Structures are given as C-alpha cells and as structure tokens.
Length: 94
Image (cartoon, rainbow, N blue to C red; front, side, top):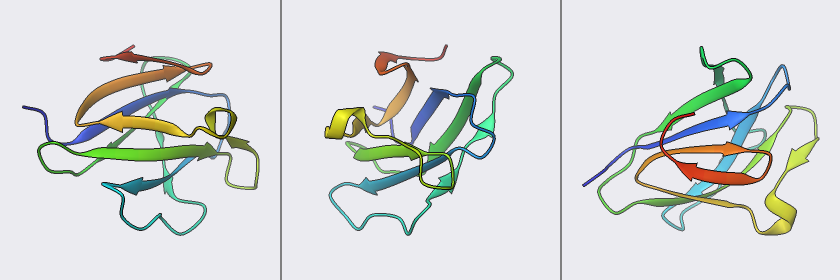
C-alpha cells in the first residue's frame, strides 16, 4: 500500500510548479512546489511525502500565472505514482 504521491507531468514550461492541497488540507502558498526535469524528455517530476491512503488535489502553473487546472476540475492524485500528459492521467511512470 503506497504512501508518497509521485507525479510526472508533461510540460515545456521552464519554471513549472505544482499547487496543491493534501488530504483536504491547506493549499500551498502560490506558486507552489517546483517540479524538476525527468530524464523522460518533456516530463518533470515531484514526490509529495504522504501517508497511506493519501490523496491530493492539484493545479499546475508556469510560475507566473499560466495555469493547467483540468478545466477547473483540478487533478486528483492518490498515494502511488502517476503520469499526467496533455490532460490524461495514467498510473505509473511515463
């Protein structure tokens, strides 16, 4: 049973950030946490420390007010690993 929340995100932004609320808690202070490039070209990655049975709600930004917020639904990610690319989420790595 997975614990941390690891997210891969396809983006060409140079300063991508994840803004999120973990387990229905407080949201990060803007602009949120930076994502660091993965060796999967075009993808950035973050791992959010979390307990068993965790879920976060997230929106991504370019550090300067351009957003990807899933048409206002925001993106939901559970304990485990997930890859978001052009609005589609698949479990696991790229």
